[PDB]
Amino acid sequence: KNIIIGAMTALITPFKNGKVDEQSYARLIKRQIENGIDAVVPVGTTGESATLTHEEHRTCIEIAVETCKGTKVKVLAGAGSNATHEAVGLAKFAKEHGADGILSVAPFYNKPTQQGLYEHYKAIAQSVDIPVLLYNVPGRTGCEISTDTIIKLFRDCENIYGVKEASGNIDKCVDLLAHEPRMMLISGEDAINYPILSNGGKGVISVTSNLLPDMISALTHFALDENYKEAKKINDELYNINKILFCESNPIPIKTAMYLAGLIESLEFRLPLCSPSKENFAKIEEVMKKYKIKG
Amino acid sequence: KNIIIGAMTALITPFKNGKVDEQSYARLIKRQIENGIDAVVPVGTTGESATLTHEEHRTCIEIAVETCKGTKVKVLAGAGSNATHEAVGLAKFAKEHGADGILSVAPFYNKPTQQGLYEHYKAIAQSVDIPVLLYNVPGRTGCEISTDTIIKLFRDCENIYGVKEASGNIDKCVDLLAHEPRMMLISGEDAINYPILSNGGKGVISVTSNLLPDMISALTHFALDENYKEAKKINDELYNINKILFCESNPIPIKTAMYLAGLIESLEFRLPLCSPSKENFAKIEEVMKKYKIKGF
Amino acid sequence: NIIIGAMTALITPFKNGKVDEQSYARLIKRQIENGIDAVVPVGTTGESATLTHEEHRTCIEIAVETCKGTKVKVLAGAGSNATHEAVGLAKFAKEHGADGILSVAPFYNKPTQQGLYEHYKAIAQSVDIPVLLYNVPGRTGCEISTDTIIKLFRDCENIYGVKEASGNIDKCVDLLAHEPRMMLISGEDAINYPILSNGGKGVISVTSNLLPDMISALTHFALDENYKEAKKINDELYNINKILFCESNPIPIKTAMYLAGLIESLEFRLPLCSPSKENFAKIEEVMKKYKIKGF
Amino acid sequence: KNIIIGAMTALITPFKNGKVDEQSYARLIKRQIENGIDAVVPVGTTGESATLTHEEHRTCIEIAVETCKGTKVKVLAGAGSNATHEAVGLAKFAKEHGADGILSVAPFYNKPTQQGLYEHYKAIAQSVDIPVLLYNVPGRTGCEISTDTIIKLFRDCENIYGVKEASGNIDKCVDLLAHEPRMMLISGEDAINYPILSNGGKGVISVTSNLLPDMISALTHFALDENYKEAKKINDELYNINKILFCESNPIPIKTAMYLAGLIESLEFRLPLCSPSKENFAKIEEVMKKYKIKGF
Ligand SMILES: N[C@@H](CCCC[NH3+])C(=O)O
Ligand SMILES: N[C@@H](CCCC[NH3+])C(=O)O
Ligand SMILES: N[C@@H](CCCC[NH3+])C(=O)O
Ligand SMILES: N[C@@H](CCCC[NH3+])C(=O)O
């Protein structure tokens, strides 16, 4: 099956005076390209997909597809929804508008059964032909795509090729690849990028890469090159930034970090997201003072 | 402060051929109305708000308002979203179209901070001049509105009057009312309706009441009338059905039970929701046999 | 035959390492002087884990003699994660004048529900005094399931109920809806009233070390079905009830006793120890809200 | 620091007629030595430490010490307790009767604070002069030794050299080795042996090695040799046995498997442990027969 692996970036969606800032967005994607990043994920969790209108969401996917066209870099379009008909709609759009594949989050809030999860993803996979990456983030969704379901879907569906794991559970990671070595396990948690990669994971979808695309890109390629000494080295030194970028909900801290680095104009969120508390603000800028940020 | 309390129902949304069965929807509300229900909650979690379009969502509110108009049964409209701008738009439609107040779920999925939660609700509360009931269901949303935030919202916003608590945390309920006895604590967890009411809760927003509106109605009014022995009696009897209705994700069992009772024509959901396992179907069917289920 | 009502998990006071036995008697007298219906020598609040049998059994004796000739009963701590030990403890408490035993679920070793049944069955059959089960999964690492609690209650005459310390009011509804004959005892102070209002017949309290009159009043107002008054006290008590667990029980309660001049010295036996300076201030501050009894 | 690393086995404690089968114990330890284990852990959790008397506890250690004498195999004695005086008492015997070091579990049930955990272990480490390995298993104890606490103990106490981690938390394993690279991180969770080792872990204390000591020792040695591909392969192969060895509480499945393998005479537990459900019995037999088991 066709895949999208390697060092991938969960793009922040910068805001300017309320509206999506289409210049910085298309610009930041270029900064990711010119820094060793293999793929970009428009409008994921980090891109505030919840606060974006279906039009704005569709716009960002299109921008991402258009800024990358003609490069090595791929676009993994965030197409998740807790309503299957929307997710399909977002899936069909990405395909008909030229994304390489889609990252489809597990339905949040409505807590579907494993059966419902299977049919949800089957419907999405069987309405496009592009690679589909599952996304398991139970802390946010209130639901867990079981290994059984994940593997079931991988086998039943031609274009479902893996899962972005952000469940903090390395046991599940071993479980996945022990019973199903053919799948692409993607790290969805920055602090444990290395352990996932060292167990056969084939890439990451990073938040930290927004700030430090070089460090994250190198880590993954070192790990993929099976240079575990160097990949662990980077993972170890990135531990502090990886943890501090979650002292409050992503993408709050990362945007704050992208702001302090001059990479974006305004520290601007769409409610219910907001700027962090001053304490966590102090903690971020301090940790930032320990790394070399490029622009 | 103006409020909406008593026996309330988280209305299921019946589908027929994929579309909302509006006649059936109106009819189910009538059944709730005539069985002692004080207010109805169109399009909550139980009404599959996640998979309705904004237009269907708005229609269900219209149907609910139209059906309760003339009765003193209030319409507490589900207006929550994980986007403040959506939540405000929904809250404004609810106001403009006759809803007596709204129910606003804590933002799900995007895990806002307590600061973000406060501003999210303040923005909503300032948008309309009708009662706003907070909704805390951390198991679904991935976030918890802390007791302190709840009390701040209640004290800072004139139309925020309470919270539907669905966390299975009785300590929190004790915490809420020990510090702010003026707020309306609403049970959103059927199994423990009585413990919440008996600690000062002033109503329930029930899933069970779709099937047994009379029993839930009587439970709440016994409790509200301080007849705790009779309220507890009913709560104990309802424990079986109260648990079985969550053998899978609400509203999967309740809709199955409604279908089994002949109260809705077809057992249809919108994906990712679907019919329960054949086993749970049999378990629900078996548990129903222990209860007198009022018809239309 | 049962033990219900307002019960106190007695603290075990230390002076220079050894159990201050005069302080123990004075405290127990103080509990009796304030309407407490039963005392629990050597519970978790009594630091059973760090005591020797020489002391575990000294304490029980003192409890028996101090209560000898009053209406106040003695529910001895007699639990262990080893059945042969718990049986020995059960037999001791009996052979030494205890009116009943409190038996915690086996901690650490995580027995099955089958094992939990065979454990308690062997305990109840060893002695002829009533046995109160103790469920505190946050401490033990296991939970006695509702079915297991009910089976034990039905299969053994002297198993008459359970001290519940799981903060799960649903389980309390479950237990009393299916087995309304058992004595559900509250083991979490903050939610004493909601448990009592659902048919609970008593509390085994930490706060009643400090405020025995109020806890005794609460429990008795609820037994008389004056739920209005029981709720008032429960609400007044919430703050002290919560602060008494700002650190692990019995660290805050012993600190409070010390601050109230009720024990000689703030002395724990390791691994327990003094609270942080911060929590010391918190505890001291919270205490001011309350009128505290002397001897 | 004096250390004890490598492939280690949490020894089962076989009972015949209620008493510790001393001869079978030595026979099992001998089998471990022959199949390449680096250390054995007498009377830990798997050793049913909870139900053994002090006489038996000490007896088991001495058997482990005397069997390992004249070999490279070390004895890491289980010597934890949730009372510091008893833990020091246990520690003092283990040191005086041959054990190369002690494994000391975090105080269970009484939940001491981080400050308490520090003073607990400091009192242990400064009362005997043999290596001490911390044991963090919060699911059994109810408390967690924080990363900061572990590093403080490592730095302020000469003979504390690392921690057996059985919390299924790889993030914590990263935090530990990233801030204190001299830490001897030992896997205490068989299913994640490889991921812990691949991050700089220096050993395992295995339940599975009782049954398959060759595979566990091969896994650990491969990982220490930077041969991650082969170490992962084995870990992947062992995943199912590593998981079903916990369908019921350890050491219930492992002892069952050892009995069905003919490695011990009888399947006796001391209460509150007991024989598994007859269905879990067949489950264990099923999984074990999918592996190659060494005799004596
Ligand atoms: N805020 C809603 C709608 C999002 C529409 C697509 N960006 C949600 O998170 O599901
Ligand atoms: N599916 C989106 C939009 C729902 C719109 C109708 N309530 C959500 O769950 O928020
Ligand atoms: N600390 C040991 C011994 C307690 C002795 C008194 N029962 C335990 O809790 O198991
Ligand atoms: N049940 C006690 C007994 C300890 C005796 C020495 N192993 C405990 O686990 O602490």
Image (cartoon, coloured by chain):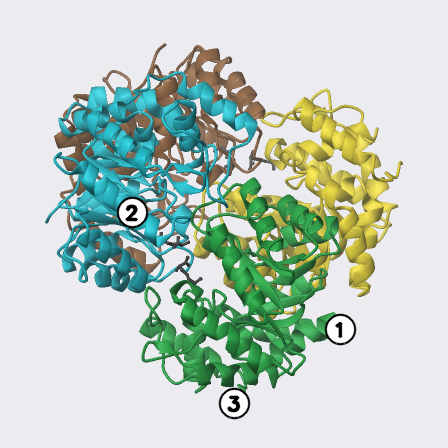
Chain colours: A brown, B yellow, C green, D cyan
Q: Name the residue under label 1.
A: C226
Residue at the spot of label 2: D59
Extreme residue in the left direction? D1
> Residue A5 placed where, x, y %?
29, 20
Picture residue at 26% right of the left edge, 23% below the top: D215
Depth order, front residue of C153/A21: C153
Ligand 2 rendered quadrant: top right
Residue D105 x/y as whole percent: 31, 51
Q: Any atom of ligand 3 within 8 Å of the CB at mark 1?
A: no
Tell me the tag on residue A33.
Answer: none
Same-subunit check for callouts 2 and 3: no
Image quadrant where residue D222 sits:
top left
Q: Where is residue D54 in the image (x, y as percent from the top left)?
A: 34, 54
Chain under label 2?
A: D
Task: Identify the mark nearer the N-term, 1 or 3.
Answer: 1
Residue annotated with mark 3 = C294
Disc 2 versus disc 3: nearer the observer: 2
x%, y% of residue C61? Answer: 52, 75
Quick check: can you spot residue C282?
A: yes
Distance from the alpha carbon under mark 1 to that under mark 3? 28 Å
* Residue pictured at 27% horizontal, 60% vertical: D89
Total count of labels: 3
Viewer-nearest of discs 1 and 3: 3
Q: Which chain carries label 1?
A: C
Q: Is residue A9 visible?
A: no
Q: What is the crowding at mark 2: few (fewer than 14 residues within 10 Å), some, or many (at least 20)?
A: some
Identify residue type, mark 2: Thr
